[PDB]
Length: 508
Ligand SMILES: CCCCCN(C)CCC(O)(P(=O)(O)O)P(=O)(O)O
Ligand SMILES: [Mg+2]
Ligand SMILES: [Mg+2]
Ligand SMILES: [Mg+2]
Image (cartoon, rainbow, N blue to C red):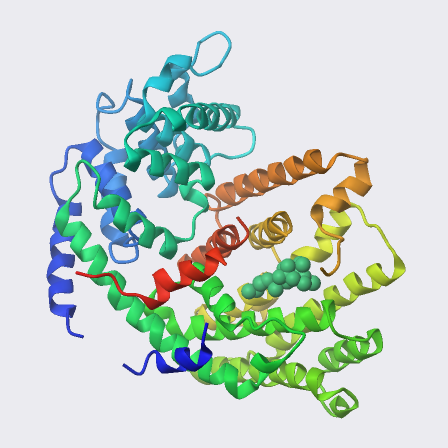
């Protein structure tokens, strides 16, 4: 990554009329007659190509009327149709019971019938649908285990390279857990080779992708300029994480109309990865204690006591925090500086508890560690910032409620932390080793336990999305998509993902 070259991008196309024509056509298709299984497959194709943000209402209405049609003959007895309907309806907020899978099980033992290994597409759809489940839905747990076992069994026996690629991709990460934009870039190429491929939808996908990528490149140019202006790229003992943070933010939100929010999120992310290193890599406890005190008091009057290599990240945090709070004051009429200050103070207190534990040789339980680490991962900061920047009529009360980390937000933060600990030269007190110290458990027993925690908290997020809350569409999607971006990173192979998504356009 030549940041010299990324300041280039965004400085330097009219396909927008054809884009609007293709959008009207795809929209008519979504409203079109569409025998119901074909309509489901089309809606799911539109989603996988990253186009749901264009056709929100049409997709919702189409799925709502599919749910309310008078007859079930078109999907019952059909595993692919049953699973796809389950998943899409339950993604749309329309509950479907797990009972619909019982007719594919041996009615005595509850096991899915081994003969289903003859239906690869149905197995894939059952697999994908299983990750829409909640706690206590045992049929969906069984569906996950069975489908994964069978798919890995037959992956070597599949001779269609396209379907082998799809099966391998699903085994890497289920669709429910995948970052939308990167998955869209992958599935454009995949969809171009599918059986019932619709060329109108494919062309619109490619064109819309290039346009959104143009917005992204302008954003990257501005952010690289700012980041060089901070001088933080030239820190020897701190990660140069501007482009990594922007990739995180793309996973969190990719819509062009949210661009400015992205930039701020990106900024915060960068600073997070810098300050963490200040706390994890190169910093005296006296230096970090002073860092934390200054941040808690929001008072930079004694900042010159710090060496300039620490003084620059601290003051960049300070000034960017004030800038974002003032953006809130100006554009939303609400001074957000106290809340950016609060979230940074809380995150530095979490960093401080972690560093103090290390120096003390403390070995916390997994629960204690996680209580601190859902904050130290930084996503309370990022999510409260996104809420500040996007909520209608911001108030002290709304901000206090979101910053209290209710179950929905707290589950997303926990997931980000434990996913990063599964993906992880620093502080070796992470999730796995905390559990090992707790229970004396094995390396791999602890790892599988943490993976089970991943599944459990995803179940809780799924059930949260069905339950009333004072949160609305954009923040909802933010909360899910930070977990998806975490899955994206801690599965450089991430570098070439950035090249394919943010740098190179799609040839048309
Ligand atoms: C974009 C904001 C999240 C990016 C990841 N941050 C660096 C978190 C820091 C960590 O996760 P990292 O593993 O050091 O990257 P930590 O485990 O030290 O808390
Ligand atoms: Mg770290
Ligand atoms: Mg750390
Ligand atoms: Mg770490």
